[PDB]
Image (cartoon, coloured by chain):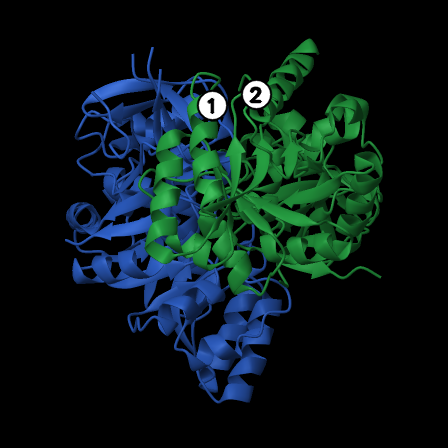
Chain colours: A blue, B green
Amino acid sequence: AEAMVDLGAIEHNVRVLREHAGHAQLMAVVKADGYGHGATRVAQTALGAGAAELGVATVDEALALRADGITAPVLAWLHPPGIDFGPALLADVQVAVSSLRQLDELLHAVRRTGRTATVTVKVDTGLNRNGVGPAQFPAMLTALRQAMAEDAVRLRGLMSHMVYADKPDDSINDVQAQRFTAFLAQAREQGVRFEVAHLSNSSATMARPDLTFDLVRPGIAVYGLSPVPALGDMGLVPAMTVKCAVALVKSTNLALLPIGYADGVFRSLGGRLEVLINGRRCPGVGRICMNQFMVDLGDVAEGDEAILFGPGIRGEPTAQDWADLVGTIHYEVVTSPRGRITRTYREA
Amino acid sequence: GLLAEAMVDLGAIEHNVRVLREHAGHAQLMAVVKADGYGHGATRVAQTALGAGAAELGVATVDEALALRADGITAPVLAWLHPPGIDFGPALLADVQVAVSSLRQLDELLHAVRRTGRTATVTVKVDTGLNGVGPAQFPAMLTALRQAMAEDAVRLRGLMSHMVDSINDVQAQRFTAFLAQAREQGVRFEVAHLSNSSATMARPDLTFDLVRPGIAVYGLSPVPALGDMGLVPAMTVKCAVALVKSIRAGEGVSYGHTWIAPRDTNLALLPIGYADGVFRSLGGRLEVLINGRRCPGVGRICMNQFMVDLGPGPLDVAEGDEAILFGPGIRGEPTAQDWADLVGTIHYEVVTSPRGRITRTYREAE
């Protein structure tokens, strides 16, 4: 079994996203090991296709990209209490801070390493998770101005998280942008200029160009998965195809597929999913086991290829179809395949 | 792993193996460590189970068996799921026992015996109602094994089947018929085994020479309706609290704002999500244990984080404090079975889920 990532599709999706972003620079989001597609290979491909920067949640993710030889800018924005920012600084990793405590921790690491931090501030425009709130932003701006005066930080970015990953027309997107503009006015009042400001995820990138600031941060759309499923594929091509070989044929006629829920085939797909074998759809029957399940063939031989999901070009189910059956989202579908499902690549 | 961990208590594994050996009576135990030890770590659990009296190990694939061998495991290892056209040579050269479930597979194994010159320690997997050799094909299987055994191409170690209520008695009766058909055709196996964890613990009258528990080794109940059956779940999934914050009544939480605070309250941010194995459908249903108190999840589970409600009572949580998502339940935390109930699955799938930011760690047995 394998989870075949078509880097040609990644490259195509990156090119589509850049058309929508217009003059804005694109930050390809490759957290969670490239949403299960492989952070390093997707990153290399996106940068080749015109992405300017990479975005990840954790410094650990950023250090992994650096260790694989990535030299492009990388921004990390989720830091657990206790983190040592020193390794990030020595590896030229940009850090988004979301509290004065995080800033103070970063500054101690700047003095320790002797390395000026390229810093972004993450503010709360409505998600209400971890961004700096409006009342705390002035104090943060003052501390940043002081630190920048002593050449301890370079003030690169202002960023915020969108509330809706898939609801572009909701006026909360417009509200969050108005709130973001207000934060920028607060900075002006404190004599601070950020190099760039960014709020857009994939949904906002493709559908709200009127809310684009200096950079866009698409993730899901890089992998070809529609950020607004009710609109169809949005001209993207899902990059991941999950397939496995028929391990046994047994008589109707059934095929044994040797992957199961420990490999990420959601157990709740039992008796509901279909797979594509030699052009035809074959429904799963019976439970998904830990490492195998059966499908009903109703012209198939041991070793033949069964496709569980993909872009849909050959009539195979899509990750969205799995999301529909399971009651989830394709984000969770593509971060599931593992174990016996080996990640592979189709070169572009 | 500082951020989050799936901590496996090897003292619990030892206790569970001891319990299983008690139930197995005179029979020996094959501890089943397929799927990287049901998410607990095949090698570490294998080492601990053998040290607690397990006689042998069971896995699905030869690849799993080779991984144990490469980590220095020398005990017997049996593999029973093989892709068509497998070259059994490496298994024979690594002293991996092979269970065959078809005549075609036996032919593949006997070819590998001819190519390598290594006798195979063979087990036949028969179909008692569940793959497997069927009654129709078994007479031809026995004639061939008698032939291979006479030239010492194989050592005839095992006869096995897998259990799929009187249906249990029916499979056992079919299994005994296989043993009789082999005995009357003069083909003797060293050992016969039918029993998984459920049979081992609940149907001792159906114990043959060996039992093959998996799930109960990890302390998870093989008959959940009967309770913990004296076993202790070995996996505890826990994470450090990354942020504590206050919110006002009326404020939304997490992507989509699917939860609106009915009152001013305090929340904690736990930095693991569905890409780490926290099923997204647990959103708004699961509870965590923090400093002895249950805290419900609020809002959607995100890719790598979610939020829990600490309540508006005096704050008793700090950043860096420990949140327990599930465990054996000794401290009042949820169990893997609780998760299985909430999302409509089985604990087998729960414990094979944690990954990503959830680092597997080990507590040594005292």
Q: Quadrant of residue B129?
A: top right
The answer to whether marks 1 and 2 mark residues whose Cβ atoms lie closer than 8 Å is: yes
Q: Position of residue A329 (x, y in %)?
A: 42, 32
Compare residues A113 and B287 and report the one nearer the observer. Answer: B287
Please name the amino acid that badge 2 sits on. Gln
Compare residues B296 and A310 and report the one nearer the observer. Answer: A310
Residue A198 in view here: yes
Q: Residue at x 29, y 63 (%)?
A: A53
Q: Position of residue A156 (x, y in %)?
A: 37, 70
Please name the amino acid that badge 1 sits on. Phe
* SS assignment at label 2: helix
Q: Residue at x 33, y 37 (%)?
A: B84
Q: Residues within 10 Å of mark 2 (few under 14, many from 20)?
A: some
Q: Quadrant of residue A107?
A: bottom right
**Disc on the earlier residue, 1 or 2:** 1
| Residue A278 in the figure: left or right of residue B226 | left
Q: Residue at x 30, y 70 (%)?
A: A70
Chain under numbered label 1: B
Q: Please name the residue that numbered disc 1 is placed on.
A: B138
| Residue B100 in the figure: left or right of residue B187 | left
Residue A298: mark: none
Task: Measure the C-alpha gap from mark 1 to mark 2.
Answer: 9 Å
Residue B181: mark: 2
Residue A193 in view here: no
For marks 1 and 2, give the one nearer the viewer: 2
Q: Position of residue B276 (x, y in %)?
A: 53, 47
The quarter of the picture where the N terminus of chain B appears is bottom right
